[PDB]
Image (cartoon, rainbow, N blue to C red; front, side, top):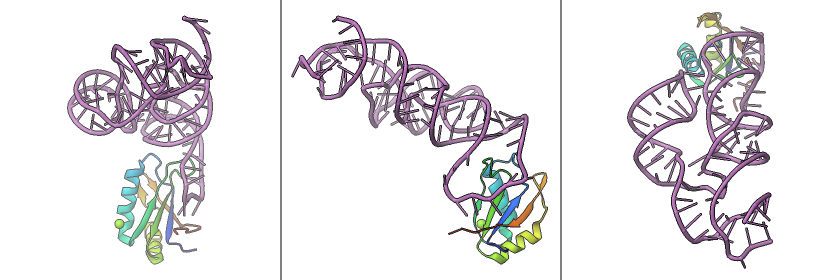
Length: 87
RNA sequence: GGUCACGCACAGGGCAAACCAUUCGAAAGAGUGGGACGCAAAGCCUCCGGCCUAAACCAUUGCACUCCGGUAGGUAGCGGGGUUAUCGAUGG
Ligand SMILES: [Mg+2]
């Protein structure tokens, strides 16, 4: 189950990539070092984001702490990524 | 001479990238003026394949790391194709 990456669901689709990545970084940087934040705004990737943590514990902390956080109108749904493939 | 090609020329010459100023545009970018990287169609057309932007509208609750909805705008100086044009090596 636990992954270096957390997967954020239910994000506001009307926010630009630039500002969304910027915000997501402000939200999640306080839980630990982030390797990258993946945001695409393609049909398949809309309203979703991948935050990749240096450490699994700091990924687990973010998920536990920030479930359903009011974020640009919508409550963030967070799960672990199903796979990692950061390599 | 005309036509379909072709570009090693010759003649007239033509266009104008980046960057800047300014205007329109949510943006990509486009218009105009200055400016030349280059260009034998770098004249013009978005029918086809790409690439870029993606605000609004419609749709989508979606697990990616190759990129990808519709729609709309852009690129004709990314390519194809269409159509029009100067000269004529001896040039085919
Ligand atoms: Mg950081």
